[PDB]
Image (cartoon, rainbow over all chains, first blue to last red; front, side, top):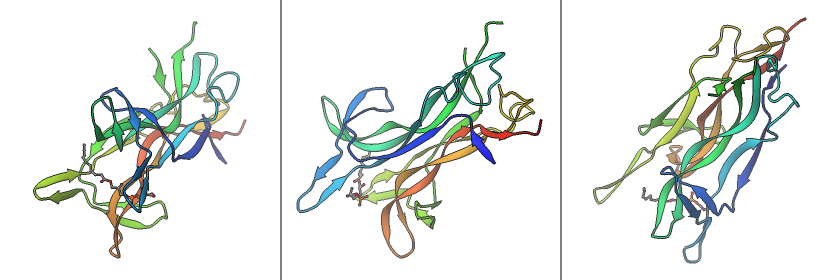
Length: 108
Length: 108
């Protein structure tokens, strides 16, 4: 009977258009690549927060006495065909992969 | 000056050989492709848990009184070039991606 401090939602994203690369640059994702009688699509498995506060208090199961808390996304980096102002290239881009809890010393 | 409820450590993995694909099968990852001496390497950004218990009562910031808790590694899925000894193909494979706090209502 386990459970999570923060709630995830997962989605297959087949139409991403913008993203931030591992150098922190904003880049455009080429979701579709019409290479002749064939079409290549880029899909990403993204997991994000259902909400930044599961409970009004912040994250579920937290000691709201001494701890402020919120639920936030973390990321991995995945290679993706992209373009910037200059060139098309495979670049590592960040994508949401999990929802996690952020703490913070309470004002006490 | 914020705190994580689940401590993680991240590495880059560039010599992956074995994995589990999204169909649950065990596959071989082809780390490098050599084309005319030009070498394409696959790298994976993996995030795992430091320990199941950062704090001794499991996760940090948890109402130890009402809740039992123990951080744990979760995964995501990532395209990689692989073979199942029957075929070489890009398959979505499982990747350690975050360290999250698991909730368990203890007996009051």
